């Protein structure tokens, strides 16, 4: 393992919203595959369904479009039509409260799912432990 194994509570029984306190945005996966953040709670593309492939490993999927969150070889987030190795994330507890999602494929490089204060996605290499951009809070739909 390249990372710790503290896991958050809760489960995957219901769809969730992923809220980033960094800028105060909900993770959004647009129909065209674009990924970003939005402060609009009524947005139809922020509803996500998480599922566990293995303990601590998850897929994050758009309930509206069916697309899977994924991080490409250059660290950019994108919506994938099908599940592949770039769609698996390590879901962990952080600061004894939040949820962090580390790219499983690039786990050794410490690439996290994260949003900047302006709601734009952070590129993998620009993220690291200790940032506010990587801290998520799952919220009911």
Image (cartoon, rainbow, N blue to C red):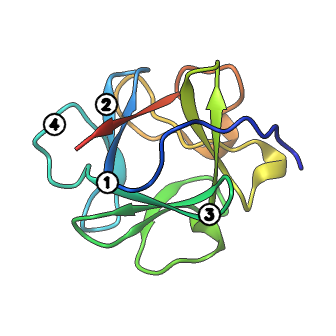
Res 106 visible: yes
Residue 27 locus on image (x, y percent):
35, 43
Distance between the alpha carbons at the discs numbered 4 and 1: 14 Å
Query: What residue sits right under mark 2 in the picture?
Result: 25
In the rendered image, the vertical position of residue 43 relative to residue 60, given as above or below: above
Q: Secondary structure at mark 1?
A: loop
Seen in the picture, residue 130 relative to 20 is either above or below; the reply is above
* Residue sitting at x 55%, y 37%: 9
Residue sitting at the far bottom: 82
Dot 4 corresponds to which residue? 41
Pick whichever, 137 or 114, lies toward us.
137
Tell me which numbered mark, 2 or 4, is placed earlier along the sequence. Answer: 2
* x then y, percent, for residue 26: 31, 37
Q: Which mark is residue 88?
A: 3
Element type at marker 4?
A: loop
- Of pointers 1 and 2, the one earlier in the residue sequence: 1
């Amino acid at each position: 393992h390249h990372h710790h194994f503290n896991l958050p509570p809760g489960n995957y029984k219901k769809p969730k919203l992923l809220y980033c306190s960094n800028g105060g945005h909900f993770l959004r996966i647009l129909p065209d595959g674009t990924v970003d953040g939005t402060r609009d709670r009524s947005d139809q593309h922020i509803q996500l369904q998480l599922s566990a492939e293995s303990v601590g490993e998850v897929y994050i999927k758009s309930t509206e479009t069916g697309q899977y969150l994924a991080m490409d070889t250059d660290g950019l987030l994108y919506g994938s039509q099908t599940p592949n190795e770039e769609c698996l994330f390590l879901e962990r507890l952080e600061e004894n409260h939040y949820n962090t999602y580390i790219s499983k494929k690039h786990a050794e490089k410490n690439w996290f799912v994260g949003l900047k204060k302006n709601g734009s996605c952070k590129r993998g290499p620009r993220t690291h432990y200790g940032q506010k951009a990587i801290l998520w809070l799952p919220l009911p739909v």
